[PDB]
Image (spheres, coloured by chain):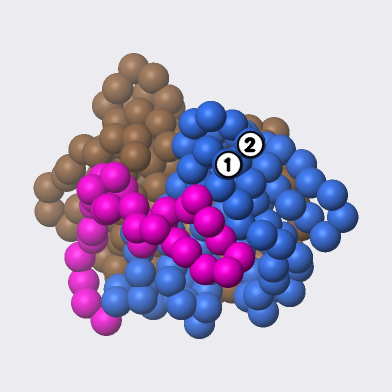
Chain colours: A brown, B blue
Amino acid sequence: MILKRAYDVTPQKISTDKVRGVRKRVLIGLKDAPNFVMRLFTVEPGGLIDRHSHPWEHEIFVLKGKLTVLKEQGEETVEEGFYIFVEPNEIHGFRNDTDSEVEFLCLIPKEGGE
Amino acid sequence: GPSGMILKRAYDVTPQKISTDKVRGVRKRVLIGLKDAPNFVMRLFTVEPGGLIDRHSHPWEHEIFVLKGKLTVLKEQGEETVEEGFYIFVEPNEIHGFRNDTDSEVEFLCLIPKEGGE
């Protein structure tokens, strides 16, 4: 059994043409997980994960702040205490329009990698 | 399966009493359940003050994230208390359980492969 403070997992900066101002912690990764992986994303103020889609679903829980969720059209802001289920193939992305960091858990089946 | 995205306040789900020979003082919200999940389910457990999930094991793993309070984790050997912001991975067949020794509700997300139900 593994019991660990998530903050102590070293975050990975992601900074690409589609993703800026994001950090990703892999809490339960391919090394441990039989079926699905557990990540924790931090989105800095102004951070953006562009619209994209995957052949797998996402299961998300918003841990901190106000997360702007981009949909195939339009967007919806939700806050800490919301869960999100993104169906397979659904176009989606995320933005932080607030002045403080936003955090969410994001789990995918292991075919999506870690 | 279907398209779209569900976005919902977890507390808009009513916490339902779990009562079995090995569990007392616990409620559960199914957030992403069997009716929708392709692979794995997401539940939010509430452990009332003095609530107990006795040591047990399952043939599937558990992935847990502690949301609120101080959760005492029962292991095959001894116990350990963690708090909000901890995650827990429980291997398949690993003996584990939980207790709330505090005065206030403890909450944690618990995800399992959907073959284990919801």
Query: Which residue type does callout 1 highlight?
Result: Gly
Q: Which residues are magenta?
A: B1-30
Chain name for mark 2 = B
Q: Farthest residue in the top direction?
A: A99
**Side of B41 relative to B83 (left or right):** left
Disc 2 + disc 1, Cβ < 8 Å: yes
Residue B28 horizontal/vertical position (percent) = 41, 57
Tag 1 residue = B50
| Co-location on one chain, circles 2 and 1 | yes
Q: Nearer the viewer, residue B69 or B55?
A: B55
Residue A62 horizontal/vertical position (percent) = 38, 41
Q: Secondary structure at mark 1?
A: strand
> What residue appears at the point 23 percent right and 58 percent down from the top-left corner?
B6
> What residue appears at the point 30 percent right and 73 percent down from the top-left corner?
B36
Query: Which residue type does callout 2 highlight?
Result: Asp
Q: Nearer the viewer, residue B76 or B10?
A: B76
User: Which image quarter holds the N terminus of chain B?
Assistant: bottom left
Q: Main secondary structure of the magenta part?
A: strand
Q: Nearer the viewer, residue A17 or B91?
A: B91
Q: Farthest residue in the right direction?
A: B77
Rate crowding at label 2 as few (under 14), some (14 to 19) or many (20 or more) other CA atoms within 10 Å.
some
Q: Farthest residue in the left direction?
A: A74
Residue A33 horizontal/vertical position (percent) = 66, 66
In this picture, is B21 found above or below A91? below
User: Which image quarter holds the C terminus of chain B?
Assistant: bottom left
Residue A55 horizontal/vertical position (percent) = 38, 73
Q: Secondary structure at mark 2?
A: loop
Tag 2 residue = B101
Inspect the magenta stretch and tell me whether residue B6 lies in it: yes
Chain name for mark 1 = B
Residue A106 shows up from this direction: no
